[PDB]
Amino acid sequence: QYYKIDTKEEILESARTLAYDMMLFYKGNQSGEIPGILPGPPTEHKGDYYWWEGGAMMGTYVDYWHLTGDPSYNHVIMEGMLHQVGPNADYQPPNHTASLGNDDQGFWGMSAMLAAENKFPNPPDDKPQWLALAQAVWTTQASPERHDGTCNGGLRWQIPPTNAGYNYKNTIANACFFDLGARLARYTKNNTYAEWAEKIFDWLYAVGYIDHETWAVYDGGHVEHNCTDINRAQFSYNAALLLHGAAFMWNYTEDQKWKDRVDNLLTGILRDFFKDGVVFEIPCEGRQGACTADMLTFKGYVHRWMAVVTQIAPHTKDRILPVLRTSAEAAVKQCVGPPTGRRCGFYWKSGKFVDPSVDHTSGAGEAMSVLAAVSSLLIEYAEPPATNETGISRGDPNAGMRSRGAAQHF
Ligand SMILES: [Ca+2]
């Protein structure tokens, strides 16, 4: 094995090197390139990765600095986050219309929310602020045209009615909106965020995307079938994002129902996604050559989000931290690939390095996931997410409400 993770110092060093190797994939800070995205999209033969994965990368680095204290990449990350906000400061840049799912937009909003929670340095005074960006995403997602009567509610996957997939009401779109609402409630102490989060969670439960018996979290269903044709694929990030938002709701409300939901979701995750102590992407990881670029990133989110759950729902700590530790041990055990002797693959449970070329990418998602897992080993030393009591960001009461906003010409 290359990386050592048996002391705080060793973890910091490993995380710093993993942060370097992940940054090698990113060209957006170089002259002539576009800040905030990884190479791509593959539809243009520019690289393997879609726009939202750039947003995921940004958030990974906001967490990296929070967890390690290393500010080396902060300027690059601020530039990338600010470049992608769109003319209306809502993470709906129209050049990216084909990538404007509610989940895609949501992941950028979540990275802005994380920047506010982590006290990431503020953008310049004339630029959109982190809390305001999260509020804009949430507000656009709360807009009435995104909540119709099909399936008795829920967000559709896609924002544009003409985008393929507009007929699919899926967990991840709704989970992003839920998580943002829960987090905005905690940060701002505004209950309207929480009431929306409650409503969307209750919808996810009612429609049966959350299994009422097992608390498995399925993928979605289509409006033409009243959402009854449930795609029962269980992607790790869906259950983990609901756990994350439920933990924020528990912390904010202190309502036992939210504690119960945290505990049930957590039981399900530990049962379904951890195999001998290692996170495992059940719909695709069982053989090589099945996971898509997007799927290679999920286990990193699982680690980072579950780590935060231990801070804001502390009763979960002893259920979560030991399992994240064994999972991160497996992650680093297989970061031994050529040509560097430390290249990271995806198949952590297997115990062996597998070249990312088997899954048809350069390996940025695998690198991001190991960076996330190793950095999050430092959660015991980190501050919990800030609220407006100690945060330094600023909001906007009209976030998402501009007259040129896309909702005005829907
Ligand atoms: Ca490719």
Image (cartoon, grey):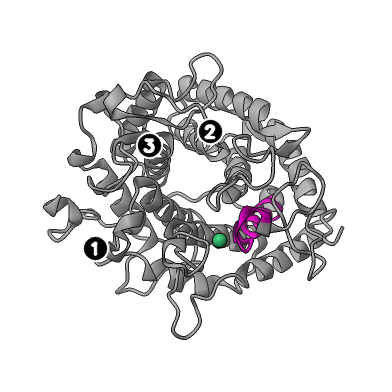
The answer to whether marks 2 and 1 mark residues whose Cβ atoms lie closer than 8 Å is: no
SS assignment at label 3: helix
Residue at x-position 48% and y-position 30%: 250
Q: What secondary structure characterizes most of the magenta part?
A: helix
Q: Which residue is mark 2?
A: 239
Give the Cα separation between the discs numbered 3 and 1: 22 Å
> What amino acid is found at the position of numbered circle 1 in the picture?
Asn
**Looking at the figure, which quarter contains the N terminus?**
bottom right
Residue 81 or 125: which is nearer the viewer?
81
Residue 93 position, x and y percent, is 29, 63
Are discs 3 and 2 less than 8 Å apart at CB? Answer: no
Q: Is residue 28 above or below residue 211?
A: below
Element class at badge 2: helix
Q: Residue at x 37, y 75 (%)?
A: 124
- Quadrant hosting residue 23: bottom right
Q: Nearer the viewer, residue 109 or 385?
A: 109
At 75% from the left edge and 50% from the top edge, which residue is drawn? 331
Density class for disc 1 (Cα within 10 Å; few <14, some 14-19, many ≥20) is some
Question: Is label 2's Cβ within 8 Å of ligand 1?
Answer: no
According to the picture, the residue beneath numbered tag 1 turns out to be 88
Q: Which mark is residue 174?
A: 3
Q: Tag 2: Cα neighbours inside 10 Å, few (<14), some, or many (≥20)?
A: many
Give the CA separation, mark 2 to mark 1.
31 Å
Q: Amino acid at mark 2?
A: Ala
Give ligand 1's quarter of the image. bottom right
Magenta-colored stretch includes residue 373? yes
SS at circle 1: loop
Q: Is residue 402 left or right of residue 8?
A: left
Give the magenta part as a residue range. 358-376
Instruction: Classify mark 3: residues with Cα within 10 Å, few (<14), some (14-19) or many (20+).
Output: many
